[PDB]
Image (cartoon, coloured by chain):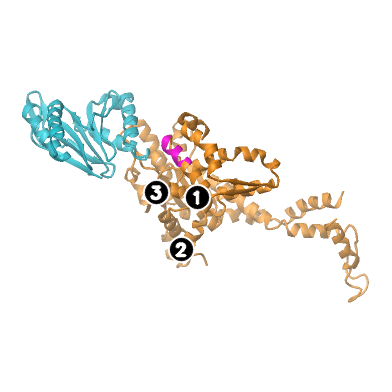
Amino acid sequence: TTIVSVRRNGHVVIAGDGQATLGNTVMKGNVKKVRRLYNDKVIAGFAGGTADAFTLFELFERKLEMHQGHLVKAAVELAKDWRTDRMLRKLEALLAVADETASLIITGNGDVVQPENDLIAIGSGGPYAQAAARALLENTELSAREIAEKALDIAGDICIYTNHFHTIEELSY
Amino acid sequence: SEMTPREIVSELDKHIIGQDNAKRSVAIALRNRWRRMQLNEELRHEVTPKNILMIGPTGVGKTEIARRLAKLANAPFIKVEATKFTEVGYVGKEVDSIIRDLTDAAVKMVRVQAIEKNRYRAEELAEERILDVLIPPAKNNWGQTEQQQEPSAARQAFRKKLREGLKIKDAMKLLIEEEAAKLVNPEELKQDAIDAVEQHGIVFIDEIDKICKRGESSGPDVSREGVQRDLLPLVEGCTVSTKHGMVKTDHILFIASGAFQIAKPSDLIPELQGRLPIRVELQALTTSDFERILTEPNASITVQYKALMATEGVNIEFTDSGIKRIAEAAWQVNESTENIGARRLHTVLERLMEEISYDASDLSGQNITIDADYVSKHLDALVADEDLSRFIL
């Protein structure tokens, strides 16, 4: 799959495709890889278990609960539980979460990464997404949503594991 | 003839800064208890307390509100940590202890409340026991019926000569702890408390959110939710075995409190959600908020400090810029390290005043002035050194 987050001006987005693959066949084509959390204040995307995500997004949203809402802290506190607990440690998936403050990547390896210009591109198509998301953010005035989306379509074109079904979320401030 | 909500909020304003909604909330609870007493027997049974759930960050007013509310209603009050009971999966303790602990405090009250409302009469009759071992013209009559009757004459000048003047004083106190007791009725006193608990009890349950779900694990959620289950009867209406009697939780007012950063009130057990009909949020405090807390409350910390120092014959004065400076510090530390709400003020205010607090007795008669200069000199360094902050502030 491919998830692409971009942040320009007062907008930050997270777009993802809808293909779910098994072997060499497409299982589903309209999977919802992006969603809103923490009273719509937080937007996130996931690459992997359509349920593993569920479990994760919630716990994450449990971190933001009694930690004011500090995106970064609750994010590192999550990867912490994630890499520890046998339960959490069991599930595998790439997490891409953003918010007014900043966007970052969370992984099972208890890793909390924040790409260069808050530009995230995970999933089997992340590279393609990023290469295109770059060429644009670099030589274009296009909005965060226009790049995320245009970059996402480019990925879908190259990546055999990503389709052109989008699911975008945004955040304005 | 109780106060109206606006009246209740007002009084609350005298101690708590901001958090208006929470006040109106906790205020409607109180008023409703009055409202209920004003109905027919039938309805008086059907109308139960409108229990409240406060949602908000640490030290921003939750408990203070509940505490002041209870105070204003002269109601027995008790605070309790929800997670305390999840421990029962090892040994912990049982929820019924809440009503039990509540009653015990409800007794300690009715007691001190009644004994104090007596220490004055017992002292007066006490002297009437001493002013009897100095001039005993007891019995009926003695001299005249009118003029000569009044035996006070020498006695009067005798008691005064003693009041302002074994050992009278040593004797009276002994008589005080003999007449007071010989005046208390421990029967109705035991039931007095129970009635309180049953009609004005206020139970504060902190960490309600820590008793919720989370895809965590079977074991833990089972321990957590159990505390919720064990809470149901208290809140739904039941009877508890009191070391001093039998209490009906039926009309006790419950004020639960949760951050809900991790968990949402909707994760709470259904039965509970039903019994927490009122939801209210409290906001994080602002530096401005802080400045007001430091001074506005009528027994503010700043006022306390000034008083404490006066004790030592030292006059303290807080400049506005001084207060502002103090407030910013607390905020700065809370943001740079860990946000603990208004609590931070006490730590800061207290570190700031150390040198004086110590030298106090020596500056007897001086006019110290804590202005922005002083504050900065004393706190700026500490506030800056983060690691030092996590120890000293």
Callout 1 amino acid: Ile
Q: Position of residue B305 (x, y in %)?
A: 60, 46
Badge number at residue B293: 1
The residue at the far bottom in this view is B146
Q: Chain of mark 1?
A: B
Horizontal side, residue B42 vs residue A83: left or right: right
Badge number at residue B6: 2
- Give the mark, 3 or 2, whose residue is nearer the N terminus: 2
Task: Name the element at disc 3.
Answer: loop
Q: Chain of mark 2?
A: B
Q: Quadrant of residue A109?
A: top left
What kind of secondary structure does the magenta stretch mostly adopt? helix
Q: Which residue is mark 3?
A: B283
The span shown in magenta is: B329-336
- Give the mark, 1 or 3, whose residue is nearer the N terminus: 3
Task: Name the element at disc 2.
Answer: helix
Asked if marks 3 and 2 touch (Cβ < 8 Å), the reply is no
Callout 3 amino acid: Gln
Give the answer, above or below, for where B327 lies relative to B30.
Answer: above
